[PDB]
Image (tube, rainbow, N blue to C red):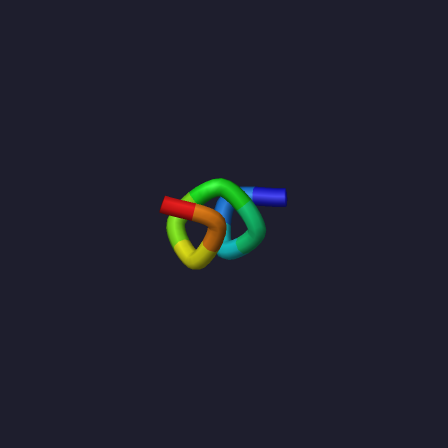
Length: 9
């Protein structure tokens, strides 16, 4: 989840 948020942004 953390990486999803980071990459999405």
